[PDB]
Image (spheres, coloured by chain):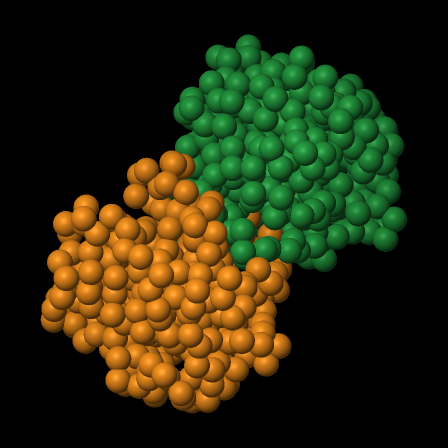
Chain colours: A orange, B green
Amino acid sequence: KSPEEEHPVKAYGWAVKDRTTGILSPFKFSRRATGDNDIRIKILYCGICHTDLTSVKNEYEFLSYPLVPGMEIVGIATEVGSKVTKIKVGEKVAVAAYLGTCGKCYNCVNDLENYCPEVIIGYGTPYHDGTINYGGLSNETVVNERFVLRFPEKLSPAGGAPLLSAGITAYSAMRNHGLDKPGIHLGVVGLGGLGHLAVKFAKAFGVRVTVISTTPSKKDEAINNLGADAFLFSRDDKQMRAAIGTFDAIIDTLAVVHPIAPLLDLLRSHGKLVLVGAPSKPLELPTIPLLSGGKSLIGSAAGNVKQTQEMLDFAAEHDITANIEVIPIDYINTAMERLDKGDIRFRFVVDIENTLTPP
Amino acid sequence: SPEEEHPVKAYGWAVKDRTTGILSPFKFSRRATGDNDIRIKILYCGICHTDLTSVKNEYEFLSYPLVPGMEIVGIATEVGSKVTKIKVGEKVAVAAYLGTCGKCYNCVNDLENYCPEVIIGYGTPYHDGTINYGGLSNETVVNERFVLRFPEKLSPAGGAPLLSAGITAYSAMRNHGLDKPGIHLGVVGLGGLGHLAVKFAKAFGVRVTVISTTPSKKDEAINNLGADAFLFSRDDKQMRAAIGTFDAIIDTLAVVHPIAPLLDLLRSHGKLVLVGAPSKPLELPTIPLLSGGKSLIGSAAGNVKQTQEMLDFAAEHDITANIEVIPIDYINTAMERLDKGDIRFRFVVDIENTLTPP
Ligand SMILES: [Zn+2]
Ligand SMILES: [Zn+2]
């Protein structure tokens, strides 16, 4: 069938129609009717993350096109299924970075569902009904209540949107591995959308933070704007040899290939290097440092919906928001170009309600 | 000069030309017994892959002539004035390392094997600047801190490989909770380290699947060792069937090899423990690591308190290595066989009866 015929309820947004160019354009489609456990969401803001860019750059083999990207959604519940009681129509809600899970593995039943082997990602893949999921650059969406969050009333809807993928990924990796207790000297490699949010949460956790980066012109943003206690330029072997053995843990946010040996030397014995960015190619692990130091390489991806709701409540109390540029949807293609060059501090957020036009 | 460097004469075998790797008879000397030192008459010295890598000229920092060997079992012949833990004439063993700085965090809390300035068994300077000579020699002198009491009821020959291979397996399991029944543990590589990892797991009551590329080890793994299962690491069907079934995996391989298949074998949040030291670097796929939320963990040997505790746990549960006792002048042939994995599972040199005086 056609996108507008495939489902009963009409919907519209922007979508990459030709995967070889990556250009989004207005797109008409449809969404399933509200099930008994479903929430219909009028989308207000949609953050743009690196996953969107990679998708747009035609580097995701499995994705179906036309592709409606966007997986950091903030909106309003317009309709709720018969069985839904946690949310009422008219309340502010947010969507998790994933839309569903098998529901029968250990992870799912113990509320660690983001690690389910059969996790359904925000968009580009089939749902439990076989139909491709359309993401957040659209006027409305429908999501199972389990994967819909309650948005704190005292949190900027626009500024809170990037928390739903970038935020949770940093929050969960820190909480789950004990990088949230005051006293720790924590390194954050890479000052991007993910990196800048790792710094904000650490400061609100009371953690000493050195921003590790290549770009030396980010020093001012790292210290003055973000609140980093120190800054390491990753070319000055004087700085490097001085910091050897000084870090209890390091969060690596880099999406690009990069050496690992220098980062392990920066750790004290039994220190942990947490990888949360998805490198394009595989990196090379230096066994000699890992073994002699007794160090750990640890991967982390997003977080469970219970963590996501707890993180959202923790950001209202401590006024944690992202540094965002709110853009109209027809600026998306220019924004993608700027994101490809790192020409953003630090997060695009599309205003869906006011800049998306029906037809 | 080697014969003059210290007052007391000694002899062994050594690699004189680092470019060939051939050991030959070698005369040298050792320091006099300090106030806190124990002199050990060496009986048996295990041979590990570290020795082979050393003789294969893959450690640039090692000084030559190189006397290898770091799994020493012997007898204390004479002890310093202050030494009280050991009595002359009792069986002793040496740790895989010879000294530490003594004032970093690791040192002062008895985690000294992770000291940044740890002095390895041989080939690097001691606290007095002189190169250390390893266990393929007639006697050694070691600070009392790094000398262990060898249980009387334990084979000196079969116990020798515990001091590097054993402790490395023991500590990696104890430190990461791979010693409590309920765990499905994988052991990659059925060599000296791998086979001893299996024995300790059985005595811990842990379920052990041996993962190997050599299908001819299946019979020894299951019947002789006691492995609960055996997985051929190139049999895709077998591998794709075990996906997600392992709580942890101990990787003992000294050679470069893919890790992505080993990560799929782990359940979410599972741990891959590295105890083998490949010369070259491995290729780390981040997609499996991230999506599964898994961990890559390195481990090296263990502390002297653990090493003594491991030695006491092996006496009680009768854990020894499966060894071939060899004369010292067979060492060059033994290295060749070890390079091809033609051993089940550990060479042990008989120093007392086969080392000839100078
Ligand atoms: Zn599941
Ligand atoms: Zn030390």
Please tell me which residue lies in front, B71 or A330.
A330
Q: Quadrant of residue A313?
A: bottom left
Please tell me which residue lies in front, B251 or A49.
A49
Q: Position of residue A226 (x, y in %)?
A: 28, 79
Q: Where is residue B306 in the image (x, y as percent from the top left)?
A: 45, 31
Q: Where is residue B229 in the image (x, y as percent from the top left)?
A: 61, 22
- Name which residue lies at 69% across and 37% down: B236
The answer, for residue B233, to whether it is visible in the render is: no
Q: Quadrant of residue B194?
A: top right
Q: Position of residue A258 (x, y in %)?
A: 57, 69
Residue A337, above or below A9: below
Quadrant of the image containing the C terminus of chain B? top right
Please tell me which residue lies in front, B19 or B84.
B19
Residue B195, above or below A105: above
Q: In which quarter of the image is residue A206?
A: bottom left
- Name which residue lies at 48% across and 39% down: B267
- Name which residue lies at 38% across and 36% down: A104
Residue B77, above or below A168: above
Q: Residue furthest top?
A: B153
- Name which residue lies at 57% across and 60% down: A62
Question: In the shown orientation, is residue A342 left or right of residue B32?
Answer: left
